[PDB]
Amino acid sequence: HHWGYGKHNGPEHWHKDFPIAKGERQSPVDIDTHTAKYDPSLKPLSVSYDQATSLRILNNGHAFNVEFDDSQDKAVLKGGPLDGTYRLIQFHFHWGSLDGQGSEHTVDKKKYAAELHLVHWNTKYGDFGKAVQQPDGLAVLGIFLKVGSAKPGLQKVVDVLDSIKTKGKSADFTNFDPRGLLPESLDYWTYPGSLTTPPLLECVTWIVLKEPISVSSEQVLKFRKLNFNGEGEPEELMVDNWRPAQPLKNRQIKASFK
Ligand SMILES: [Co+2]
Image (cartoon, rainbow, N blue to C red; front, side):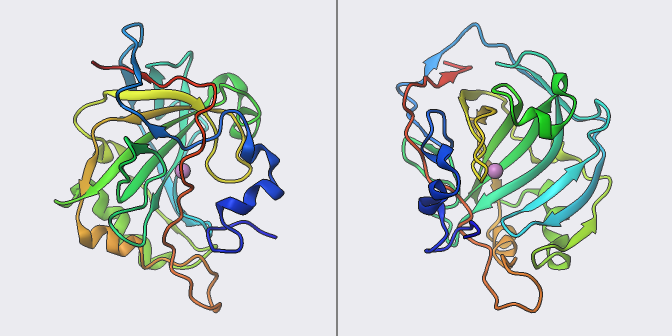
């Protein structure tokens, strides 16, 4: 049946409809920091979000996506391990029922409270649906969230969530600046992997930032009041929407820093 994160349709079941789930380059993974190799051949990341145009925020039943206008090169990622230009299409988060879990990537087996994914697609493939069919189709910027001080730039997101509580609800969400979600440092780890939700396609260059951002308990608590279900269905809190770490297999994680 339809996939989700419960006991009967969670990540351990996905391989039955999506056999690539047991593939050779599945995400997320544990980042073993001692084994990642510094690659001095790696460039600095180029995040150019000055002209970003957010449009809408949507509860899609798994997460909430903040969507952007990607019909022009307004918000792009380049540099780092990437060839070419990748356009921002949406960002979303993965989070836990408790502060001790929620991220998808782990760092020396450490789990963070949440993980932000800024999803970008390679403009050489013309649109997102074509890009996910290519091994270099997507570039996803992963940022860990730890609980501590509030993230001022997150509050506009937190405050609209009660308007999209249930699956299928959307709201206008313009003039949101995703630069306010970035940590100070852009040091990163990178490896080839996959989408972390079905269809689990192996099309992603992952770029995971070393430095987490901090958010407050109140901010993450508001994530946890969302619902997986549709309006007028039994309430299932949207929590623990993370896939756990998958086998690294024949892959090397590279680090941009020493
Ligand atoms: Co994600």
